[PDB]
Length: 99
Length: 99
Ligand SMILES: CCC(=O)CCC(=O)N[C@@H](Cc1ccccc1)[C@H](O)CN(C[C@@H](C)CC)S(=O)(=O)c1ccc(OC)cc1
Image 1 (spheres, each protein chain N blue to C red):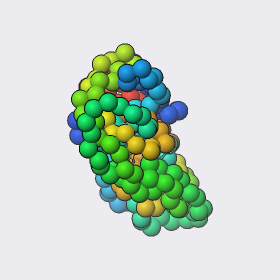
Image 2 (image 1 turned 135 degrees about the horizontal axis):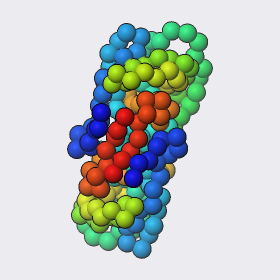
Image 3 (image 1 turned 60 degrees about the horizontal axis):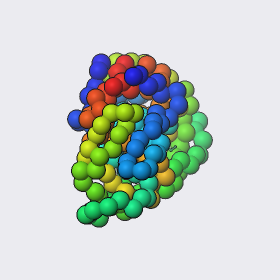
Image 4 (image 1 turned 180 degrees about the horizontal axis):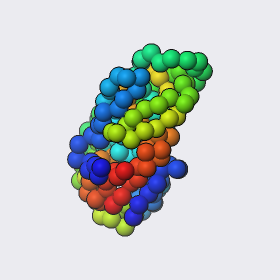
């Protein structure tokens, strides 16, 4: 799809058979989801945003279907204010900025 | 133009006699610029992201040129680590997400 920006670019994602809304976030290097359970090993990681640094759990090679497009990559889980899809997965689904 | 997201979507912006590099950020409702002493009236505000909130100064009707495209609108000024071009201005320069 083509998505304009007069509204937040929120989309439905499917992860672990659960549907969630997430924000397509070109200003984010990484994909960060609010607290949730995911299977498998994770690693403690810290990441920084506008307000400072937080602790997250890093899960690798996680399938997410974003607006019908398949990705498999790294998903960080922690106290993000909103679910965000970052460039690591935006590139997988072929997402570009155009003007 | 089309900007892929293999790397951060940094572009050159101009605000008065200051050229800066800024992120085209679909995850940002508003435009947030690094500390700079702009002329005119402003109002204090707090904006939140990963890590918590920062305090900013809201200036209205500031002209900004983004890759040669003219824009004018609200800019938030404060201790952000990166200059952020948010949706309020992305729409003005005709910026969409596509995949
Ligand atoms: C390398 C570090 C990152 O990639 C961190 C991801 C991130 O927080 N991204 C921000 C933009 C940003 C980029 C670098 C450093 C600091 C911030 C994100 O794209 C926009 N943020 C809002 C997200 C998290 C959704 C809530 S923001 O905090 O910067 C923000 C918040 C409010 C706002 O307007 C009201 C504008 C921008």
